[PDB]
Image 1 (tube, protein in one colour):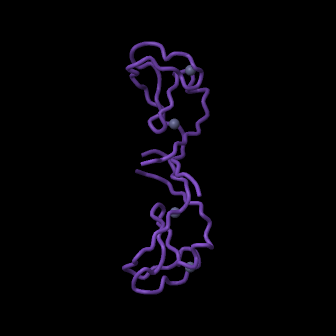
Image 2 (cartoon, protein in one colour):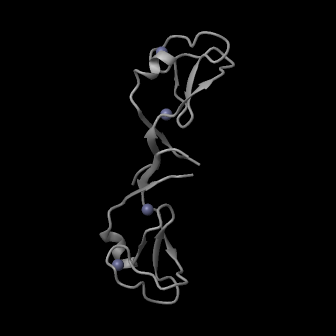
Image 3 (cartoon, chains in turn red, blue):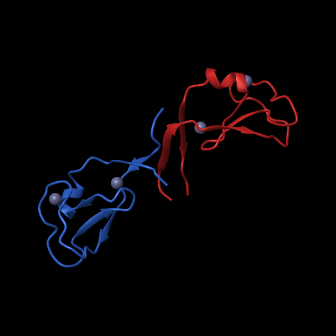
Length: 65
Length: 65
Ligand SMILES: [Zn+2]
Ligand SMILES: [Zn+2]
Ligand SMILES: [Zn+2]
Ligand SMILES: [Zn+2]
């Protein structure tokens, strides 16, 4: 691997959390036992459904693979 | 929306060109039958040794895989 970043926009998908998880935008618990929020398939950001429109679309992460 | 890109700096490595190939910087032939120049391991840019010093470091490509 080299110094490198992946840069794009988020790719959020409905996610079923198996452990208590917080929103990476607002900090409140992702309530529920299933489909509690959205996780970006690329960078892993977790958000409430209602917080999706509050977050910037920019999605970047360092690639070490 | 946006494309996803892999971004960093070039990673040039000496390459054996099997067909006549030109420098992507200056346009002159990569002279010889072996080790004629360097190919960026990330984006594929081909350069003369001397042109390595002349190109911008910026290395980007769209990731379609
Ligand atoms: Zn993301
Ligand atoms: Zn939230
Ligand atoms: Zn490159
Ligand atoms: Zn050249």
